[PDB]
Image: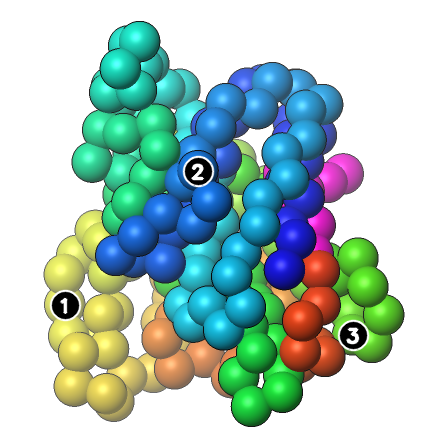
Amino acid sequence: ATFEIVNRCSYTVWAAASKGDAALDAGGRQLNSGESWTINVEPGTNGGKIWARTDCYFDDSGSGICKTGDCGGLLRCKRFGRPPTTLAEFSLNQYGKDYIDISNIKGFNVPMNFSPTTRGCRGVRCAADIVGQCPAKLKAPGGGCNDACTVFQTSEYCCTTGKCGPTEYSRFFKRLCPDAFSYVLDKPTTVTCPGSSNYRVTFCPT
């Protein structure tokens, strides 16, 4: 499957793509404002994620640091990134179907649209000003708006027992972005697409 990753933000981002134990394609790249990066993701990939990283510094060997979404200090991510990160999530070719979503379970850093470029399903978007409106206790100094699990490390926010409810903090994310997951047991906002669809992830879509 092809994913086109487009940075419509006015600032540079460092895109990342991983399935947690491996990079997808090159795993990461700098995207200046307006740039597009096309990656190939193997069919059958389960649990892939794409995200943006902000305020990164990398040396000539591809080692450094980002203020949001850092993946162990690498330009080319092999692992998932440090919150806060708005997440585009996908599992492809699962019994004939692809499943896509946007999640705020690991917080929010950059607004995002995640849409198919082929026929047969709709896209999803979270483009509200979550960082500007972020509750004081969730604000990340580096930028972004953390989720409550990251900040407080409680069973209720992290849904550790498999039983949890919505919270004041999850409802904040949900009010601003109804089409994104706001906590682990949120009513699913997953979209089912035809197997082997292609996609575009746009940072700062509006």
Q: Examine the rendered structure and indicate whether residue 35 appears above or below residue 97.
A: above
- In the rendered image, which residue does mark 3 sit on? 121
What numbered label is drawn on residue 87?
A: none
The residue nearer to you, when weighing 182 against 60, is 60
Mark closer to the chain start, 3 or 2: 2
Q: Quadrant of residue 33?
A: top right
Write down the region rendered in magenta.
Answer: 199-206
Helix, strand or loop status at disc 3: loop
What's the CA distance linking mark 1 and mark 3? 36 Å
Q: Main secondary structure of the magenta part?
A: strand
Residue at the image point whose x is 24% and y is 77% from the top: 159
Mark 2 nearby-residue class (10 Å; few <14, some 14–19, many ≥20): some
Name the front one of labels 1 and 3: 3
Where, quadrant-wise, is the C terminus in this rendering? top right
**Residue 62, percent across and down?**
30, 20
Q: The disc labelled 2 sits on which kind of residue?
A: Ala
Name the front one of labels 3 and 2: 2
Helix, strand or loop status at disc 1: loop
**Residue 24, percent across and down?**
43, 49
Q: Quadrant of residue 66?
A: top left
Indicate left or right for 40 with 74 as reference. Answer: right
Indicate left or right for 150 with 47 as reference. Answer: left
- In the rendered image, which residue does mark 2 sit on? 26
The residue nearer to you, when weighing 42 against 190, is 42
